[PDB]
Image: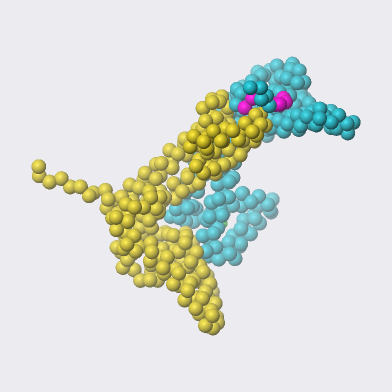
Chain colours: A yellow, B cyan
Amino acid sequence: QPEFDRGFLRPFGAKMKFLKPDQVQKLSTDDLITYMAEKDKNVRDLAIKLRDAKQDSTKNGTPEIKQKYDKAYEKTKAAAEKLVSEESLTRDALLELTEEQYVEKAALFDKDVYRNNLQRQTYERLLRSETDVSYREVARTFIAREGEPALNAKIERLALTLLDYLAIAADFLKNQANLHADDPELNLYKAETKAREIKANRAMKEALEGADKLFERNKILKSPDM
Amino acid sequence: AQPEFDRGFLRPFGAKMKFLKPDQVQKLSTDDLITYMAEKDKNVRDLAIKLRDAKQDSTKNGTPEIKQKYDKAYEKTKAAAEKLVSEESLTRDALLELTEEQYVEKAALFDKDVYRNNLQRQTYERLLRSETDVSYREVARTFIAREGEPALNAKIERLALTLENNLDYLAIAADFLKNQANLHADDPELNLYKAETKAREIKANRAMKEALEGADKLFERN
Ligand SMILES: [Cl-]
């Protein structure tokens, strides 16, 4: 009786298995692909392409199809190996990473960093999408009551004092809430953004603290006898 | 300078809203009632903008074809604004025909706090729907990857069948996420959806409770 060929992926809902970077370095190439595919969506997408290539090669082993598998396997192995490369795990290389790259790396080796990283990613995504929703709604109301040249002038005043569309849009929405403290739409955006920023900063703090514990950055100093 | 933008019946951006009880609004002039309702209702607002553009075209070119368009645009705004305060819609009998939403949406026009609570409720409800979509799409992608697309299709079909036997995408999507969360308590993506939905539902329920309480206290004053 046939099941479902998952390849290097694990069954849906399976509790993830985390190991310290040294223990992961000791894994077989196959076991490493299984480990990384479960935690990183790039290694997963590559393992799916490797699975389809393995299926084609089994059915018909023509040199065109067999090398398509060889390439697919190599690409997955290269992606998985890069995430645990000794070069990337040096104290020097870990200092060079951004807070985001540092927590995304730690999230592959620690359960709590993984969860905290997932939370920060949803709060940061909603910070961005809610700024665009609000801006496009508030700009429509602004143009209706003040005209489009008046808006372009305000956006110009912001771009002339200060980067990307979302940074200028969030500053516009904040400045207008400070100028009109009685507008419920602007004061709801203001309140909701403050609450989203609090949640994103706490998620990042938790993930960074967990990353420091994992990479052993939190216990460098020991006092001797004075 | 003198660069005065033709606002029409609209007020300056960010202007503090003026709220009156339904009896006081019934006593307003047709022009004052349009100003009152275009500030609070987006349908009356969109019509007032159409009325402003029609008045501008009629001034630019007063053809019988264009003068007829302004008159029609003014009466459409007049009717829409008048309907929101019609005596027949404010009777206890007519207010009971209204859904909790509609009742709160009507009261929002006459009370400041009901307006703020109605706005909060609308944001939290919108995010409840869009976050169910984001999660479903994420969890479905991982499900298909590990179990296959026929396996998902069978689950969605059984869910669509229990629902159609008595369609609603978000209803089906929520039920799928709920069932999977109950089956797999250790999946971080499903645990995050569950936790985030609970926190948002709490916020959405509080906003609608506070809005209904104010809506009751408003239609209580008659
Ligand atoms: Cl299900």
Percent coordinates x, y for residue B48 in the rendering: 74, 29
Q: Which residue is drawn at the image coordinates 10% and 44% (left, top)?
A: A225
Q: Is residue B22 visible?
A: yes
Kindly give the residue lying farthest to the left in the view shown. A226
The relative height of residue B78 versus residue A82 in the rendered view (above or below) is: above
Q: Which residue is drawn at the image coordinates 69% and 50% (left, top)?
A: B166
Percent coordinates x, y for residue B96 in the rendering: 70, 29
Kindly give the residue lying farthest to the right in the view shown. B64
Instruction: Work out which quarter of the rendered image holds the C terminus of chain B and state it.
Output: top right
**In the image, residue B11 lies in the stretch drawn in magenta:** yes
Which quadrant of the figure has residue B41? top right
Percent coordinates x, y for residue A45 in the rendering: 50, 64
Q: Which residue is drawn at the image coordinates 36% and 54% (left, top)?
A: A106
The relative height of residue A206 versus residue B180 in the rendered view (above or below) is: above
Which quadrant of the figure has residue A77? bottom left
Q: Is residue B216 visible?
A: no
Residue range in magenta is B6-13
**In the image, residue B113 lies in the stretch drawn in magenta:** no
B166 or A121: nearer the viewer? A121
A201 or B144: nearer the viewer? A201
Q: Which residue is drawn at the image coordinates 66% and 19% (left, top)?
A: B20
